[PDB]
Image 1 (cartoon, rainbow over the protein chains, first blue to last red):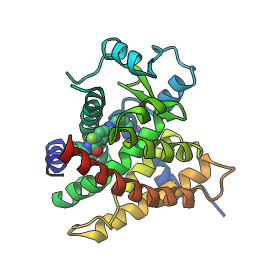
Image 2: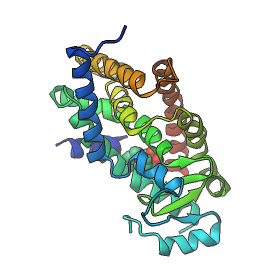
Image 3: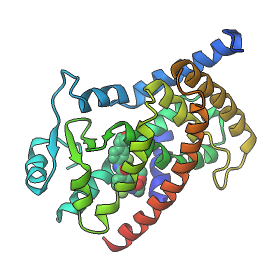
Length: 13
Length: 253
Ligand SMILES: *c1cc(F)c(C(=O)NCc2ccccc2OC)cc1C(=O)Nc1ccc(C2COC2)cc1F
């Protein structure tokens, strides 16, 4: 959930 | 009274934009997955995992991208692929017109609450009643072999199969799914969104594009549009149950 958000922000940048 | 007019052409151009992006973001399409599952491809025949011996043989003979107990090793391969899927779905979301122009916090919220619904939509493409394609089509793990894994792992994938068997009976293709998945991502009802109206405006245009896609592509299902909105409703409940299983597992394993 924190993990999931971290991966999404990484993939978005 | 449907007409081929500037508005309809713009909706077909949006549909083609999404299809092309879907093909780019998702290596194994439903077309290619169905070809593998029905033995109608010239590509390599998947290795079948149907019991503990063929799993042990498969761990060698199938080439996984990731590097104790069987149920946990399988769950960890599942966890790795899910990380890769979040990246692919994110890359797709960035191609949906208007998405990257939303507030970043809203882009993050839409993906956070949307990726699991898209994961089990796209898993259905890789499933038949027998089992699921794994390792980009190099392997096939049976539904019953997965159910035979000890609690709580044996019941992890079974609701996704139940969903898939009914979903796959609608015979959607990649052109249909590309728009379906975009509609799911642009849901203005996700918790904690800052600016809902610009998300609903994009979703409205995607709903128009989906409706037109399904009328042109599915002459013998006049209410397929309504049936797919019903499935988006069902995916909500499936993901509620999935996050409950994840909590048990993260805690106790
Ligand atoms: C298998 C195991 C598993 F634990 C998850 C999962 O939901 N993990 C939670 C999670 C934690 C941290 C970051 C991201 C997370 O989830 C995305 C999911 C799965 C699973 O469904 N794996 C999987 C297999 C195959 C595919 C195919 C590619 O398109 C269908 C997707 C996929 F996610």
